[PDB]
Image: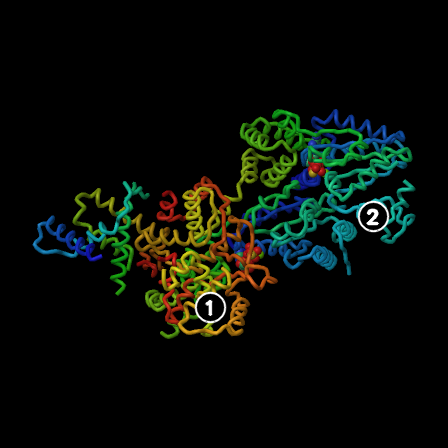
Amino acid sequence: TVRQLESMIRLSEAMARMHCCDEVQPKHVKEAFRLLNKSIIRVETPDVNLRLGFSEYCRISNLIVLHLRKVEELKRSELVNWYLKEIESEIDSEEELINKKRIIEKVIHRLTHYDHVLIELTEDPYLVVNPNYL
Amino acid sequence: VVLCRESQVSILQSLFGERHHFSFPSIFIYGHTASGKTYVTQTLLKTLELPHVFVNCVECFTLRLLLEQILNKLNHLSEITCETFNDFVRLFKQVTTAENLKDQTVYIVLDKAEYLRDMEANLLPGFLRLQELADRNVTVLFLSEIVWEKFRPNTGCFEPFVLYFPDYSIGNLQKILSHDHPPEYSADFYAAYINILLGVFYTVCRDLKELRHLAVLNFPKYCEPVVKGRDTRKLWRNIEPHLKKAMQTVYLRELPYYSKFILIAAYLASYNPARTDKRFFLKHHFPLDRLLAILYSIVDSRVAPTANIFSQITSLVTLQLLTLVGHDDQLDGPKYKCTVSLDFIRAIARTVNFDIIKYLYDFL
Amino acid sequence: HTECLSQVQRILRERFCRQSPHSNLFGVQVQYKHLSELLKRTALHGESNSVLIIGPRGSGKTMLINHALKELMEIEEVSENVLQVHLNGLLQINDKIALKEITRQLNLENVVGDKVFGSFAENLSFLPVIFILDEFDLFAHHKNQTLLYNLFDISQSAQTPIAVIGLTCRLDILELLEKRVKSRFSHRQIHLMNSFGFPQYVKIFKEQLSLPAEFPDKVFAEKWNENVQYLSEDRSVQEVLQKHFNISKNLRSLHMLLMLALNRVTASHPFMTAVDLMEASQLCSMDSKANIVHGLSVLEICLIIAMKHLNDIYEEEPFNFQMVYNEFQKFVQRKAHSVYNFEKPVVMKAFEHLQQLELIKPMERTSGNSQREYQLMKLLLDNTQIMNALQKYPNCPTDVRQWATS
Ligand SMILES: Nc1ncnc2c1ncn2[C@@H]1O[C@H](COP(=O)(O)OP(=O)(O)OP(O)(O)=S)[C@@H](O)[C@H]1O
Ligand SMILES: Nc1ncnc2c1ncn2[C@@H]1O[C@H](COP(=O)(O)OP(=O)(O)OP(O)(O)=S)[C@@H](O)[C@H]1O
Ligand SMILES: [Mg+2]
Ligand SMILES: [Mg+2]
C-alpha cells in the first residue's frame, strides 16, 4: 500500500544521508528497490564455477545485457574493452586486471553456450541478445 | 546417406559377418523419437542387399494379418493363408527351403513393437525363440521407444541383445540440417540460417523432423530482404520479430444466448461447493435441480421451462462441453461435469457482462 | 590367415548362437547317467516311466535330453521301433491343436481321417513311442488337463509302453496338477542347478573358448589355446568373470558375453585382449533409465525436478498437471527475468510426451470422466537416479541445477 511507498521514500532518504549528499539520487532508489523486494532470504548463496557468487553473476549479466540492448539503438573484444574501461575504478593491480579478464571471458562463454541468453553470429564473432530476455 | 552414424553401422556390419554365418536370434534396439532407427536400419539393409521383410506392427493389428503379410512378402522375395502360430511355423519351414534362402540369414524387421505386448501372451516369446524352433538361420530385429525392462514377460524368455542409438548434439543436428541445402544460395547462408534457428529453438524443440519442418516453413521469409535489396545485422533486424511470432506457437501448427447462461451455471455448480450456494444466491440469511435453481437465480428475466432449454442441454452434452456421469437409462437423476477452461468462461462472462469472479468461492 | 579366421568365426558362432551339441558336460554326470539309464530301460524293454526335470531357464535343460538321445538311439536297431514326438507349450496352446499335431507327427491322419471331427477314439483305442514336452507348466493351465491325464493313464496302463519327459522352470510344478494326475504321476524328479564354484566357472570359460582338435591348422590352434590359457589368469579378465558370476551363474549369459567379445575379433587382431572383454562387460551392463533421462531436453528436466520436489514435500502422494504448472510458474517468477516465458499448451505437450515415454503412469485408468488434466499421476524414478543423470547432463544451466539442489 501507500505505506510501502513512504517506506521507499524513507529508505532513499536514509541512503542519501549515509553518503552525506544534500540531494537524493536515483542510485539510492535502485538500491532500496532490491531490499524491499527480497523478502525471504537464504543464509548464503552457493558458489558458481575459481568460484564466483550468484549476485555478482546476475550483476554482470544485467550490465552486459543492458549495454548490448542500449547499443542496439557489437564485437566480443570491443565489449570486453568497454567492460574493463567501466570497471577501472575498482581494479588496483595487474593481478586483479588479469583475474577480471579471466572472469569476463568465462562468463561470456558460459552465457553463450549454457544459458543461451547470448547468440553468436559469424576471431571476433558478433554477439546478440536472445530477444526473450527482459 | 547417414551422417554422424558410423559406430552403430560398424557394429551391425561386424555382427552380420558373412551371409552363410549365423547371428543372434533376437536384437532389441531402443532409442529416442528422432534417433533415426527406421532410416539407418533400412538404408543398411538396402546397401548390404540382404533378404529382409519390413513389417509395421500397427498395420497388422490382427495375428492373421501379420502372419499373412510376412509370408506373402517372403514369398515375393523368393497365395498363402495361415491362421495359427504353429501353422505359421510349419509354412515358414516349408517356404525357407529355397535355393536363394538356403545358406543365407533371413531378417524380419518389426517396427513400432510397443503394441506387441498387447496382442497375445505367447506371441512375443514365440518370436524371441524363432531360430530354435525353425532352425533355419533366422534373425528377428526389434525397434521400439520403450526400454526392454517393460517388455519382459512374467515367465521370462530368451534375452535379446540390447542396443541403444546415441542421442544427437548441436554439431550433429547442424550438420544434418545443413546437408540438404537449397542449390540456389551459398552453403554458408544456409549454415548461418541453421545456426540462428538452433540458437533460437534448441531449448525446447530438439526433434529433427520438427525443426526441419520449421526451417522449411520459415526460409522464404528469411530470403526476402536480400531479394528486396551477407548483411548479417540487416537480416537479423528484419527477421527477429517473425521468429518471435513463430516461437509463440512451437508445437501447435458464438453460442446462443441461454447457452452461455447454462454454461456459466454449470461451471459454478461444478467448481463451487454446495454448502455455500445459498450464501451466494439466497437473498437472505452435481444434480440437475441445483443447476436449474442456479440458472433461475442468475437470470434477471423469468425464463419459462420450454423444451428448447432441454434441447440446449442435450446439445451441449453432445458437443463434449458437459460430461454425463450417471447411467444413460437414468434420466431422472442425471449427473453432469463441466470441462471448460477458466479463461474461456471468463471471456464468455465478459461477453455477457457478468462478473464470475465475485461468485467463485475458491478465489474468495 | 583370413580363411582360418572365417572358419573359426563360423565354428564359434555355431557353438554359441545355435547351441550346437558338444561332448563337454559340466556338473551333470549323475543326472545324465540316471536319465540315460532310464531311457535305455524304457527303450530295450516294454516298461514305462514318467520324469520331470526342473531348472532355471538357460541351464541347458534341452541339452541333457538331446545328448542322451544322440547317445542311445544309435545303439542298435531299437531306433527303428522307437518313435519320438515333440510338443512345445508355446506352439500348442489348445488341446485340439495338440491332438492335431500328435496325429500329424505320427502319420496316422490317413488312418484317423482328415476332417475336423472331435472324435479321438481312433488313436485312443489304437494306442514304443517317447514323448517330449517343453514348457510343461503351460499344459497344466488347460481347462481340464485332459491331455496330461490321458498320457499318465496310458503310461500306467498295460497296453503299450510310453515314456513321458517334462521340462519345467517353476519349482512348484507339483501343486499345479490335480489330485488324480498327481497320484498317477510317478514322482521322478531331476534338478538342474549350477552347483559349482567360481574356479569351476573359470575352467568352463577356458574350455568353452578352446578350439576343437578337428581344426585343420594345428599350430594356430595350439597358439590359440596358449593365448586363452594366458588370458585365463589375467586379473582384469578374472574381475569381469567375478562380476558376471556374482550377477548370474547361467551359462546363456556367458555365451552371449563371449559372442559379443568375439565380435570385435578382426584380421589385425586375431587374438583377443583383456581390454576387449572389459569393453564387452561394460556394454552388457548399462542401465537404460539413465540413458533415457540423458536423452531428454531442458523443459523435461525442469518438469522432472518439479515432480521430485512435489514427491518430497507430499510424501508418496499422487499429483496432476495443475500443481506442477503452478510451481513451475512460481520458480520462473521468483527469478527476475530468466528466459523461460512459455505458455500452457507447450508445457501440456511436454507433459504428454513425458507420459508417452512411460516414465509416468496413471492410477485407476479412466477416460472421458477425467481429462488429461486433474488426473492422478505418479513418478517411476528415484532421487539418486535423477541426481546421477543430472550430473552427466551435457549443458545443464546453473539455475536449474541450483533449483534441483534446493
Ligand atoms: N543420422 C541421420 N542421418 C541422416 N538423416 C537422418 C538421421 N536420423 C534421422 N534422419 C532423417 O530424419 C528423418 C526422420 O527420422 P526417423 O527415421 O522417422 O526417426 P525414427 O528413429 O525412425 O523414429 P520413428 O520410429 O519413425 S517415430 C529420416 O527419414 C531421415 O531422413
Ligand atoms: N552342464 C552343461 N554342460 C554343457 N553346456 C551346458 C550345460 N548347462 C548349460 N549348458 C549350455 O548352456 C547354453 C544354454 O542352454 P539352453 O539350451 O539355451 O537352455 P535350455 O536347455 O534350452 O532350457 P530352456 O528352459 O528350454 S531355454 C547351451 O549352449 C548349453 O550347451
Ligand atoms: Mg521410424
Ligand atoms: Mg530348450
- 1 or 2: mark nearer the eye: 1
Mark identifier at residue C12? none
Measured from the top left, where is residue A94 in percent x and y?
20, 43
Any part of residue B96 in sight: yes
Measured from the top left, where is residue A1 in percent x and y?
22, 57
Q: Residues within 10 Å of mark 1 (few under 14, many from 20)?
A: some
- Mark 1 CB near ligand 1 (8 Å cut): no
* Residue, disc 2: C100
Quadrant of ligand 4: it is top right
Quadrant of the rendered structure where residue B71 is?
Answer: bottom right
Q: Is residue C41 above or below residue C373?
A: above
Q: Quadrant of the N terminus of chain B?
A: bottom right
Q: Is residue B16 left or right of residue B231?
A: right
Q: Is residue C197 left or right of residue B304?
A: right
Q: Kindly identify the residue that appears in the image at 69 percent across and 35 percent down.
A: C170
Q: How many marks?
A: 2
The chain containing the residue under callout 1 comes to: B
Q: Kindly identify the residue that appears in the image at 62 percent across and 52 percent down.
A: B113
Judged from the image, the secondary structure of the residue bearing numbered disc 1 is helix
Q: Is residue B82 left or right of residue A109?
A: right
Mark 1 → mark 2, Cα distance in angstroms? 66 Å
Mark identifier at residue B262? 1
Q: Residues within 10 Å of mark 2 (few under 14, many from 20)?
A: some
Any part of residue B1 in sight: no
The chain containing the residue under callout 2 comes to: C
